[PDB]
Length: 260
Ligand SMILES: C[S@@+](CC[C@H](N)C(=O)[O-])C[C@H]1O[C@@H](n2cnc3c(N)ncnc32)[C@H](O)[C@@H]1O
Ligand SMILES: [Cl-]
Ligand SMILES: [Zn+2]
Ligand SMILES: [Zn+2]
Ligand SMILES: [Zn+2]
Ligand SMILES: [Zn+2]
Image (cartoon, rainbow, N blue to C red; front, side, top):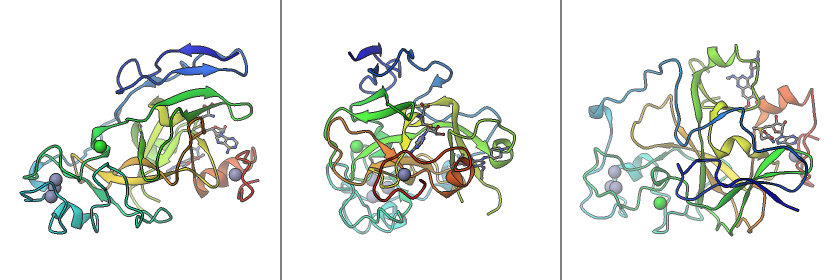
């Protein structure tokens, strides 16, 4: 029997609820963190929010032409009219995406606005058999769809170096002054996504309200059709596994598993 242990881990902060179920053991809904739908800070990050530092477009249409500056900053606008990545998008080595912003001349419904509209997919936190909690999709997700943002506490590399728990860390830039998102204490649904060696999600660096290149936001897009019921996964990368490989091996179960 599948016990519903929370009707919505996000407490109404997302468009739709994200329930938590457990059909495996007696663990209640995780409660040792604070759910936040948007990134936060403790110690100040001097993110450059000078509005005059934004690059922006002057389009008079819906930003579907090659003349859109924001599309040019992105190399091209990668979004179709449904907000999905074009099949040409390089999932193995994604570009930076510059969405339209409040300095642009265009309207709030232009083509180059997806991640800034937030999470839309029906997701569920659930108890896996041997990897703790995980996240699944409740409905089919077509390829190239925005699924969720990796949300947490923005911290410096120096701060990350003095934290005990590094299992909920995302590195913003792999030399010099770099930053991390730590989802341990503050995070959204993405903090529960498990690692997979052939992942159905890819992280993409995105700029929206600011273009401080030290601080990309991390948007997971589907790399293929995700069927209703499937567990979400992304590739945690080599730093994670160099460290945690000493303690445990990857249980993703892929025939192409690289960390077993
Ligand atoms: C960010 S958390 C993911 C959510 C986690 N399962 C939980 O219950 O909180 C990362 C941790 O989950 C486990 N994990 C995630 N992916 C895994 C994998 N492919 N193989 C083994 N353990 C994994 C490891 O304990 C890892 O340090
Ligand atoms: Cl959208
Ligand atoms: Zn434009
Ligand atoms: Zn626009
Ligand atoms: Zn624009
Ligand atoms: Zn694996």
